[PDB]
Amino acid sequence: KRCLFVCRHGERMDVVFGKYWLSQCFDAKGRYIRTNLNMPHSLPQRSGGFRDYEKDAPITVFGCMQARLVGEALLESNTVIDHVYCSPSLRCVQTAHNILKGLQQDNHLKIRVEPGLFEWTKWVAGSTLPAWIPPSELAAANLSVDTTYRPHIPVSKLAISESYDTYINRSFQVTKEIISECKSKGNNILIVAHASSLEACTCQLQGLSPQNSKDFVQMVRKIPYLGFCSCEELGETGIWQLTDPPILPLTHGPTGGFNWRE
Amino acid sequence: KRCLFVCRHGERMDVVFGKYWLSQCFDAKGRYIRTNLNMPHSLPQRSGGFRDYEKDAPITVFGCMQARLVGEALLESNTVIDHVYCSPSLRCVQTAHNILKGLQQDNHLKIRVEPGLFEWTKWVAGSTLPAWIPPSELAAANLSVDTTYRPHIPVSKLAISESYDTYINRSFQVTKEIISECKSKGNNILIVAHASSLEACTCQLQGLSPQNSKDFVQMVRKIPYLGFCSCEELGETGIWQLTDPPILPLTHGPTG
Image 1 (tube, helix red, strand yellow):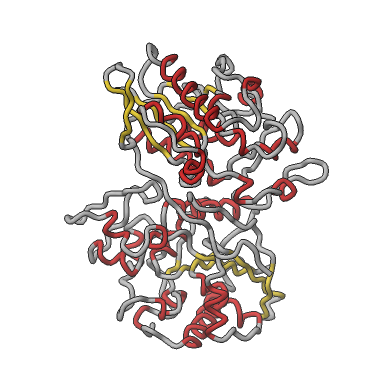
Image 2 (cartoon, chains in turn green, cyan):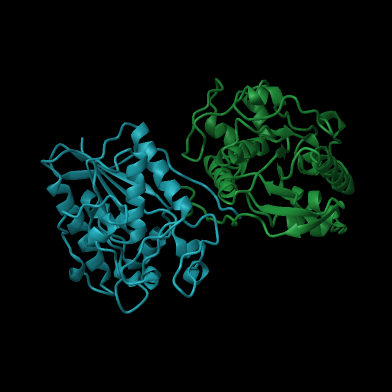
């Protein structure tokens, strides 16, 4: 009885509202003016200005709902979570926070932001890695992160535009250190990250070799928001295996119709 | 200052989970077993059995969210609603109920189920009209309907597989009776219905003639869930006009 749950972040701003959503909710003075009910009542102050959101978008209001539902589902299934890690993307942090709410654990449990959980650095448009909000600015922004946590791969140890199996490796490496620094200290582990993280984090843990970098991207655009899978360790023999999740899947469609009229 | 707001129901079971969703959440004994987080924790007992849902699907959990958000939006904009009507489809009733929650009005205000607000009866698959839940069974199911309400077009006055401009007419007729039975009795009216209802209910109210039955269906698959539009009456001269809604639009994508 030990469990690793790995799930993807919830619905993301720049996908619904697309690349330039920033011009849709920030005026010239830098004030946030929501223009759609799927946009949160407020966004966190990024110490570098509203421009930093460009390479690190937040989740939408329905993004929170997805995550809440997952947390509540988890609580209904009496599934206890002991440690919760997430990627440093804001979207991931926010999804972890909101899972903790549904779980009714946001001010008992504390998210461990692990830059090693971040997605394959190829998908970072730009020459330069996102300006992530450091943990302590994140707590200050009402997210339940652990400022005490010392990362396994800190930011500076991340190569921009890195090799595919570099990404695969760090996933296996990070997940490995996570599983063991949580061993003496209670059962179930939750990781909140990216589409790629579902495969990458678990794959070699079950002794299976990764798909080469082409069939991968295929399987990555497969994964839904709050897409969720789980692993179980037999004995403490160190061998993990795939497992039916402890909660129902979550499917829903779009508001639909016309994105635009008149 | 009088307003008619007309909006479409929220996300619907049989579209997300498709035609046979019933076999996905009811076992042989007729017990509901949800198989997805977008499925409500429970469904209302239909006096005819779980089979009645087939021609009258409920809204999904994200269906409720959409509606709630609209209600809350309405409250934030300090927009007061005085009368709320809906189509008899369960999906419409449920959307109205959930708007009233966001609005914080569910046990002050009472939904008036109006069979005249129902969609063009062509889109009823089957030889026979849906087995709608009558108002009093609906209250009994925790929806804030008015059992006192006497409908303008009751169920029996609805033709199955009816004519297009029959549908257009009843829309104009029903909306007309709604606007006037609410006149002496306070300002804003909310109708919760169908995609077709947005055009059909308002169109001739502004003196515009309807699109013929081909360009219509085009404009009907246009309209989003909780799609929302509004009308304003100038003076009490009886002339209505199009107006910017009092609340932001709601757009979101799929889980994918």
